[PDB]
Image (cartoon, rainbow, N blue to C red; front, top):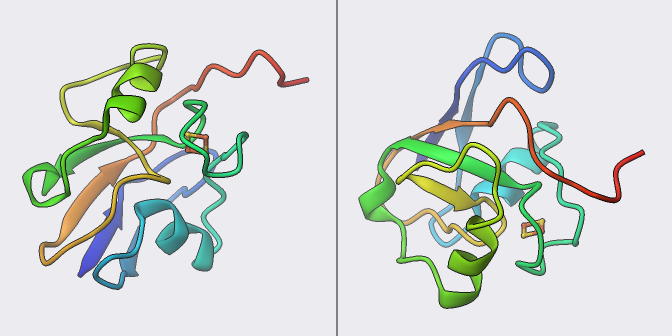
Length: 109
Ligand code: FES
């Protein structure tokens, strides 16, 4: 399915259209296309730097785990449609995704 990344001043100025594979995470699809979404804990579901908001298609994605939910409670700019992009896997529906203006990372320099 197609994943549209909304325009992001720092990581995707004009936005982008990604052709993602079913079962593939939003993050891996983004990274293959050179969209550098931060992933501090290396896709271990232990941070919130890969946080994204699924504006369209949130219901198509597999429900978030208990471990993911706990991490999201720490996410800056949390919304009902927030997901850790390293955990959210595309299924059979096109998505519209927004990368947050900021993400909390106590280890950032
Ligand atoms: S990269 Fe750390 S939770 Fe996704």
